[PDB]
Length: 211
Length: 202
Picture 1: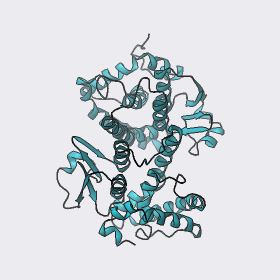
Picture 2 (picture 1 turned 135 degrees about the horizontal axis):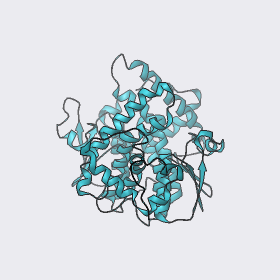
Picture 3 (picture 1 turned 180 degrees about the vertical axis):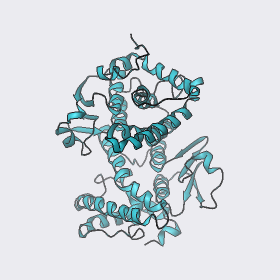
Picture 4 (picture 1 turned 90 degrees about the horizontal axis):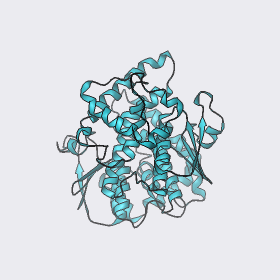
């Protein structure tokens, strides 16, 4: 019985929720209010961040560490490729996502106040530029690795969900990336892993994916 | 035939050289120089950095990515725990070392000039503080994870080799850490992986 400490609107936590729902596991999600962070969070994770996975005497944090652990323990569906060559390639993509995309997500989530407005706009522009570079991939490819859903889709989906929430506008040539986003958002495990608060981030001009 | 593009004094490249000699399979080291960096380098790695590994049509960069792939291609000796819980813990420890130690190694290796002197000192202080926290475990641990040599030792060894080279002066509590460092340096694969240029640093 794994317990996941999950921020209600935390994109990193959403990665871990999505993995758990995709795998249909026995788990308990403990909702954490990041506006009022309990002290146990910093006891379990010296960096004081969610998500955190607790299973017996095991405590993991960092969403990609947690998800790699879960994928090895419960490989159905297999989210990291089983072939070693393709797995290394995928791990390198995940690493580049963290450096080129999710450091800016962290900026948008963590830096606060009028002093952060400049860094937020830099973060929005960097994300826009990099996402636009990814877009041509999704003309030929259903998901990041082709036909099969993978950890790459898991890792990036919470950012694609939040483009409107973050005030990030893409030019029209990024249309394939948004068709890909909707392919992820239509997945039944994605629909179920969304928190009620995350559902409210969906822009007012677009309907919700349903079963 | 694995090919490793290697910086002859690059600590991240030394990580990969160490892993390759630990595994003992066939491979070729290609030295890369700045001003002799082949134009092909940007196609392999758009960040323009070594180390880079090539095997058939596979191209990898980032030392931990390269080494993790070598560890899985050639299982023995295993550089990560076989137990999934222990391995997850070790992957988390490695990730934390990148943020707590090797971001500062990168500052020392890459930032250049008088503008960088301030950040170089900040990098030296941060490394000193973290290594001081770490040192007491080697009163009781042969290697980072205990009795078994692992990727954690691989990852940290080029930094430990370079403490004098980087001008990093450790606190009085570092003696167990330095005895641990000599335990890595006396490994036959570490001796093989040292370049003539690295040997001069100590």
